[PDB]
Every structure is written in structure tokens, then in C-alpha cells.
Image (tube, rainbow, N blue to C red):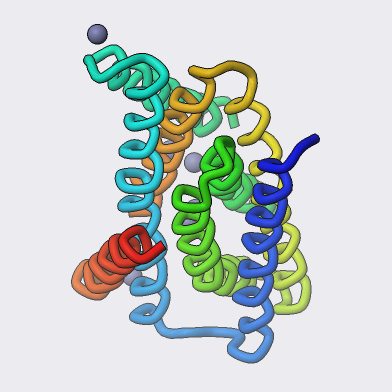
Amino acid sequence: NRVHVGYAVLGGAAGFAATALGALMALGLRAISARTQDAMLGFAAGMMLAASAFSLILPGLDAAGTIVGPGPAAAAVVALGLGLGVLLMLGLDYFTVNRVWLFVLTIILHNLPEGMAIGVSFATGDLRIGLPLTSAIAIQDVPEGLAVALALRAVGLPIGRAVLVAVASGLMEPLGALVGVGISSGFALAYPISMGLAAGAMIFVVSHEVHETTATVGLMAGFALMMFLDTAL
Ligand SMILES: [Zn+2]
Ligand SMILES: [Zn+2]
Ligand SMILES: [Zn+2]
Ligand SMILES: [Zn+2]
Ligand SMILES: [Zn+2]
Ligand SMILES: [Zn+2]
């Protein structure tokens, strides 16, 4: 309990609320074209890919560079965090009708890195770090909440149940944010390590979520918009 965790809970809350707004838009839409779905998901992926680079790895290296020094030991700390983040998510991807439940688990697992990244990115209190990432994550949460609800409906839930499950799915960002503050505030190196870890987890999820032309337009737009947000915020 402290100041920099509050900003993280607020970040996690904006992630849950953004997901929910996207989820509630499916009530009115019920179905969308494959062109629209593929673009949205490519936009969501592109936002998190650049976020991993510009909001997590690059700030984590700077944080490590002032805790440890300018040498490669700083970069080593982050890279090792990154590899541990991949392997944590490689693990979960492996150790885990009633097919709905298995799709729901994926949706849950894929929200975990975004929640964690919000909580990690606010550990030092720097709005210049947490704000671009949190607002990028909320932005792609709207398409993702919509996408999730429509897909749960496409697999056979009535839109109302599907929207409900989608909204509950978003609770994983508040929860992941709590996890993120925990792993980044134990010791000095916890922060750069946890920045690498969230980036790695994030990159694993988005590799697993990447009509290729329409998806590329979304991918490029999400990437470019992430660069804009990081530069402006
Ligand atoms: Zn996402
Ligand atoms: Zn050195
Ligand atoms: Zn998976
Ligand atoms: Zn897999
Ligand atoms: Zn997914
Ligand atoms: Zn497609």
C-alpha cells in the first residue's frame, strides 16, 4: 500500500473499463465482417508490440542503467527479465461443448501481460512511463473487448452471456496490475527485471495472436499510434 500502486490500480481500472466498453458495443453489433475483425486484432497486436519495445524494454534499460550502470550488466538484467517472461508464458500456454472454457482461458492468459505491464510501468511513479502504456493498453482494449465478445458469441454463446464473459475477462487487467506492482517493488533490480519480464510475456502473447493485408494495416496503425503516444506522453 502506497502512492505508486494507486496509479497502477487506476491504470488497471481503465483497462477493465475500456474492455467493457468494447464488450458492450457487441450488444449492438452481434456480428462483424472478417475484414473488421482482422484489422482490429492487427491494430491491437501492433500497439502492444511497439509498447513492449518503447514502453517496457527501452525504459527498463534506462532504469537498469542508473541502478547498475551504463555497461551491459544493465541490458543483461532486462534481457534476462525478458527471457523469463517468455518462458513463464510459454509455460502457461503448455500446462493449460465445454470448449468455451478453453477459449476463455486463452482470453484470460492474454490479458495477464497487459495488466502486469500497467503495474510494472508505474513502479517508480513516472507518469512519463506508465501513462503512455496505460493509455495505449486501454485504447486497444476497446477493439479487444469487442473482438472477444463477438468470438464468444460466434462459438455459440448468446450475445448477452458473451458480453458478460468478455466484461469479466477484463478483470484480469486490475488483477495483473496488482501482480505487476508486487514483482517490481521488492528490490531495486525488481523494476528493470519486471519491465523485461512484462515485455517478454507481452511479446509471447502477441506472437500467438499474429486476410493478411487487412491485418497489416491494423498492425502498422497500432504500431505507429504507439510511437505517437510514447512521443507525446
Ligand atoms: Zn492486447
Ligand atoms: Zn559495467
Ligand atoms: Zn495460448
Ligand atoms: Zn500455443
Ligand atoms: Zn488472445
Ligand atoms: Zn481473417
